RNA sequence: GACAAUGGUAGGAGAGCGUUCUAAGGGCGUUGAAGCAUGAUCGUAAGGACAUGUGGAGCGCUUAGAAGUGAGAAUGCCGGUG
RNA sequence: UAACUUGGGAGUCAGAACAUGGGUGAUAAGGUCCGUGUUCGAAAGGGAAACAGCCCAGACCACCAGCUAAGGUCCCAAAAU
RNA sequence: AGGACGACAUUAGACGAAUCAUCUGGAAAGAUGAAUCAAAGAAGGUAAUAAUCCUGUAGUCGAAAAUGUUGUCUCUCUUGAGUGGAUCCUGAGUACGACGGAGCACGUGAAAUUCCGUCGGAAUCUGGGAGGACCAUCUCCUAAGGCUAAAUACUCUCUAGUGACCGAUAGUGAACCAGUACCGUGAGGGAAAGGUGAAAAGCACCCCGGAAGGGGAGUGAAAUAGAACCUGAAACCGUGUGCUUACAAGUAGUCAGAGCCCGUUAAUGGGUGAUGGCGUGCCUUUUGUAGAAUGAACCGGCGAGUUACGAUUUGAUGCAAGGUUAAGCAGUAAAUGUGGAGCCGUAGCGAAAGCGAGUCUGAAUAGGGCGUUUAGUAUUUGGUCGUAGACCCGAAACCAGGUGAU
């Protein structure tokens, strides 16, 4: 049968033009009194999925 | 070519590797699996994305966004693609589809301003980029939504 | 330009056949793929074996896990047992696959062009057979001085030509639409009527 | 299609057994223990081709020593003298000379002694 | 022609040997096929010939295709025999 | 004479001794835990009687040719009574 | 609900072309030479391999009787439209609601849409239901009665066929008097076992022997094919012999080597081996195994990364700003033709509205992220991954339905 998308991953990433995966950031849920102004400001900015993580997860998002 | 002299193209075919057929092959015995552990077992190996109990990447990262039920997406045509029609032509969605510039219309035709228009045309599309409309008008043509 | 002969071997005229069909340089890679594809498509694939689930019986453990001194066993139908189930083995399946249409057409053209360049292309004005007669058709082949393996191409289904050639070893009869790489390649010479040649030219 | 075991197995095993011809008892008869022995034979032969050069050089040297002693000279001093004299006859030839014509060897010994 | 490299387990890469079957071509066989046995034969290896005996009717070779394709061990299964 | 980048395929996550810098233990252990090196692992050949880990040295094949290493030269046993 | 006639088909059959000679050989179909038929060169058999010897094949013909499917008559039944909007009808314990469950891809959720139990409970065309809570508007339908062929699923079975499916440890458990023998109280479990020869011509007769068995004789191409009788490997058991061995400490060989005996795919040969040097099997598992760790009595056979569908990557090939069809239909179970729905690409960015070679963030024409300033796509070999038992063997157990108090 067809391979199945990992739905949580599909809800957590977006494919860029070059094939990378844009992701959002951990530590952005609560407990903001314990993180510095700079920490929160910079955690606001999205990142990419690292190469080493991509090696592991790429098949989960092959249709994405 | 003859049925008794068939020959595939060079490099088109390669004999498959057969494991567990003796030591000289280099894939005998453990058949390239190494020694023992989960990964050596028939049907062995963990789920893709499993990190042996470390919280996986796609659970430590958060979800983002939503999908718009009424999302619209347009079939895009650039000026460089319009460059193939004869000056004076009335380019319409039907003409784009017949000419093969547009294959799937999606929510309709939007003209975008990439490349250079070199011809006077009357372009009908559901939407236009500001730059695309300016180029169409400046080349002496007309545009209409 | 090719000569057009009569069944008695004399020249009836000349015909012009597009070099874009009969005159290309044969593409051997595409031709090999086409031949392999047709041969694969001819397979029936009806082969099977019984795995351990499929072999009759075998349910019980043949003896207790420990204490008897024997190797441990779980079913008399395990693969190492005489009469046991087969591990993997053939299982019914198709061997057919597809190639792009342009490549199919290129293969047909390449086979026809190979015939034309090997001079195994003979154009005949028509087959005027009213009743089937294997002996008349054998004589026609002999007068045309054809080799053992001949593919005879008619514009459309010619009942009497087919019936006359049917029993002659090495002689195969087809139509312009029914032309295929295996037949063309297998034949040593092609004998095509003028109307068939034009029709093939149109199609390809 | 099915490929039954066929004849290849017997052909291969028979080749091993024929190579085990002459061995003691089961070792020239049963494929497993014959195969094992033929492996050991191959390893031994590889090793012994190299050991044989050692062995024959050792023999030659022993014989040269005996001849030199017969001429009141040690092997070591004879080889040093021959080297200093520029004579490159190798041990095997020296031994064969000492065995076959003693006068030639005596002349060589005198060449060595003069060089020393 | 020169001169440089060539120990090796897990493992990666490459080139090949052999088995059954198919296609096409080209061959062998009661003046004796396969199989079996023996031999002092050939190739760098897997392996390939030739001769003779036995046997009594089927089988190579070339190119390509396809796999139930190669055993020495699983207190492996079955048979035979120590 | 490598180095780096991208991509296909891995295996490995029990290590051992020896030397040396250290902790622990008793300036015990063929102990245990780190640092550094070598060898074994995955390395045959020579020496250390025999002897994975020590000393010498890295086997493409053949030779009844030569020079050496560690280690040796009265006999076993090659070479200095 | 019937009836008459006709057609076709099924269940037996019939006709059906064309070869002789010689050589080898037990036998000719083989080889050789010379012929012939073919709408028939499918196939099997016949003393070896046959288009022309037989059974057949192409083609044509054929049914007393029964059955099946059909056509026409007969038979049977049967009105079909428009205009009007006064009144009437248009499915009730129903729709629906609450609570508890269930089903919907949808786990109670914002939960529409649909069912069950319990309790409550409408409206009546100015009506009622739905468009994913709900309300309005709009749009589309008209529940709570019933029937309905075809396209779809499957094969115990019959007929005709097919296979880069097996060929006696395979293939069915079962090629054979097999669900038998045998085991079990029973449910139930469940084998082994094919081959004389063309023809039985299956060994008259004589001889030893109680017989068995054998030696002749005979049949036969062959008995060295004589009854589980084609071939007839290995383990294993015997007889004879060339070389060798009773002062020797042996993983059994290897390298060196006299003596003796032979004579080959004729090669700087073969068998044996006084004596010398060297030398603790193999596999597995280990830091490390001669290991006194594991496994194998021996020999033979059998016995483990496969296939399907997706993904990815590489090689190959076609086409290229394009590439490509799926189902379907036609075709010989083929190639192939047709089929452009769909898929991928030619544009990205953003959660989204949206804007667009730019976009998002941002007050910003700042800065920063992701992008632009060409190449894809289809099929396919190889590698790898995913879903499948997923390289093979092995639990203790768990659940369901049965069989047992001899
Ligand atoms: Mg938050
Ligand atoms: Mg590999
Ligand atoms: Mg390879
Ligand atoms: Mg290796
Ligand atoms: Mg591997
Ligand atoms: Mg293992
Ligand atoms: Mg391990
Ligand atoms: Mg591992
Ligand atoms: Mg036992
Ligand atoms: Mg079976
Ligand atoms: Mg086998
Ligand atoms: Mg040396
Ligand atoms: Mg190497
Ligand atoms: Mg196998
Ligand atoms: Mg220690
Ligand atoms: Mg420790
Ligand atoms: Mg260290
Ligand atoms: Mg290790
Ligand atoms: Mg060592
Ligand atoms: Mg030593
Ligand atoms: Mg080296
Ligand atoms: Mg000495
Ligand atoms: Mg007849
Ligand atoms: Mg005859
Ligand atoms: Mg006849
Ligand atoms: Mg409810
Ligand atoms: Mg509602
Ligand atoms: Mg409702
Ligand atoms: Mg709504
Ligand atoms: Mg309406
Ligand atoms: Mg129906
Ligand atoms: Mg077979
Ligand atoms: Mg048999
Ligand atoms: Mg059975
Ligand atoms: Mg059976
Ligand atoms: Mg027999
Ligand atoms: Mg003695
Ligand atoms: Mg092994
Ligand atoms: Mg241990
Ligand atoms: Mg042991
Ligand atoms: Mg163990
Ligand atoms: Mg044991
Ligand atoms: Mg065995
Ligand atoms: Mg797998
Ligand atoms: Mg009682």
Image (spheres, coloured by chain):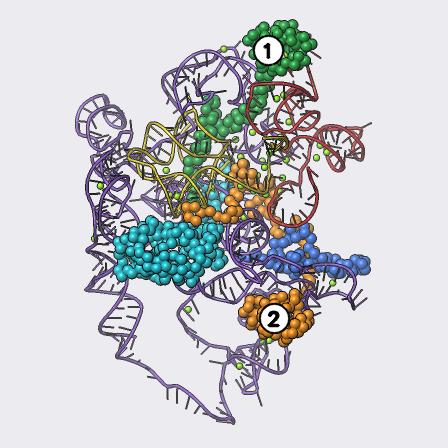
Chain colours: A blue, B orange, C cyan, D green, E yellow, F red, G purple
At horizontal 47% and vertical 53% (from top left) the residue drawn is: C25
- Front in this rendered view, residue D72 or G406: D72
In the image, residue B28 above or below residue D48: below
- Corner quadrant of residue F80: top right
Front residue (pair G296, G333) = G333
Q: Evaluate whether label 1 is on the same chain as label 2.
A: no
Looking at the rendered structure, which numbered label has been put on residue B109?
2
Q: Quadrant of the N terminus of chain C?
A: bottom left
Res C67 seen here:
no
Some atom of ligand 29 lies within 8 Å of the CB belonging to the residue at label 2? no
Indicate left or right for D39 with G153 as reference.
Answer: right
Work out whether residue E19 or residue B41 is closer to the camera in this orientation and state it.
E19
Q: In the rendered structure, are the residues bearing label 1 and label 2 in contact, judged by CB atoms less than 8 Å apart?
A: no
Residue at the spot of label 1: D63
- Seen in the picture, residue D43 relative to G91 is either above or below; the reply is above
Disc 1 to disc 2, how far (Cα)? 105 Å
Q: What chain does mark 1 sit on?
A: D
Residue E39 is situated, as x and y percent measured from the top left of the image, at 41, 25
Ligand 22 closer than 8 Å to label 1 CB = no
**Can I make out residue B134 in this image?**
yes
Between G94 and F27, the one nearer to me in the picture:
F27
Mark 2 burial class by Cα count in 10 Å: few <14, some 14-19, many 20+: many
Question: For the residue labelled by badge 2, is the local secondary structure a helix, a strand or a loop?
Answer: strand
- Quadrant location, ligand no. 31: bottom left
Q: Is residue E53 above or below residue C91?
A: above
Secondary structure under badge 1? helix
Q: Position of residue C3 (x, y in %)?
A: 36, 57
Dot label at residue B29: none
């Amino acid at each position: 049968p067809k391979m199945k998308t990992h739905r949580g991953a599909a809800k957590r990433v977006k494919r860029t033009a070059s094939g990378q995966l844009k992701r959002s950031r951990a530590f952005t849920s609560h407990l903001f009194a314990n993180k510095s102004t700079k920490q929160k400001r910079q955690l606001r900015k999205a990142r990419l999925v690292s190469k080493s993580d991509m090696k592991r997860v790429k098949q989960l998002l092959a249709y994405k | 070519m003859k049925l008794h002299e068939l020959k595939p193209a060079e490099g088109s075919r390669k004999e498959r590797n057969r494991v567990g057929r003796g030591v000289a092959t280099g894939n005998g015995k453990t058949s390239g699996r190494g020694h023992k552990g989960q990964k050596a077992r028939s049907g062995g190996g963990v789920r893709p994305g499993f990190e042996g109990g470390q919280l996986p990447l796609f659970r430590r990262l958060p979800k983002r966004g939503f999908t718009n039920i009424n999302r619209k997406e347009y079939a895009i045509v650039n000026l460089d693609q319009l460059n193939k029609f004869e000056d004076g032509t009335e380019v319409t969605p039907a003409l784009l589809v017949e000419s093969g510039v547009v294959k799937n219309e999606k929510s309709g035709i939007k003209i975008l301003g990439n490349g250079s228009l070199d011809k006077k045309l009357t372009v009908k599309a559901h939407k236009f980029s500001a730059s695309a409309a300016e180029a169409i008008d400046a080349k002496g043509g007309a545009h209409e939504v | 330009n090719y000569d057009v002969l009569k069944l008695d071997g004399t020249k009836s005229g000349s015909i012009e056949l597009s070099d874009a069909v009969f005159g290309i340089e044969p593409n051997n890679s595409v031709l090999f793929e086409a031949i392999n594809l047709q041969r694969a498509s001819l397979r029936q694939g009806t082969h099977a074996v019984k795995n351990r689930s499929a072999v009759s019986g075998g349910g019980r453990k043949p003896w207790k896990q420990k204490g008897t001194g024997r190797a441990r066993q779980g079913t008399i139908r395990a693969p190492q047992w005489r009469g046991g189930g087969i591990v993997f083995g053939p299982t019914p399946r198709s061997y057919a696959y597809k190639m792009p249409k342009k490549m199919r057409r290129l293969a047909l053209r390449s086979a026809l062009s190979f015939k034309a360049q090997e001079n195994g292309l003979t154009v005949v004005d028509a087959f005027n057979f009213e009743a089937p007669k294997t002996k008349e058709f054998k004589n026609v082949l002999s007068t045309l001085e054809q080799p053992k393996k001949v593919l005879v191409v008619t514009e459309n289904e010619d009942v009497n030509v087919e019936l006359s050639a049917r029993n002659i070893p090495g002689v195969q009869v087809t139509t312009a639409q029914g032309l295929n790489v295996l037949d063309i390649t297998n034949a040593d010479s092609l004998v095509i009527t003028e109307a068939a040649a034009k029709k093939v030219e149109e199609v390809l | 299609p099915r490929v039954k075991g066929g004849t290849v197995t017997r052909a291969r095993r028979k080749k091993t057994i024929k190579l085990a011809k002459g061995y003691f008892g089961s070792k020239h008869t049963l494929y497993k223990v014959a195969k094992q022995q033929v492996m050991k034979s191959g390893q031994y032969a590889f090793r012994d081709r190299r050991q044989r050069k050692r062995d024959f050089r050792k023999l030659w040297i022993t014989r040269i020593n005996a001849a030199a002693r017969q001429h009141e000279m040690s092997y070591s001093r004879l080889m040093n003298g021959l080297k200093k004299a520029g004579i490159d006859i190798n041990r095997k030839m020296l031994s064969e000379i000492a065995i076959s014509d003693e006068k030639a060897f005596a002349q060589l010994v005198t060449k060595a002694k003069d060089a020393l």
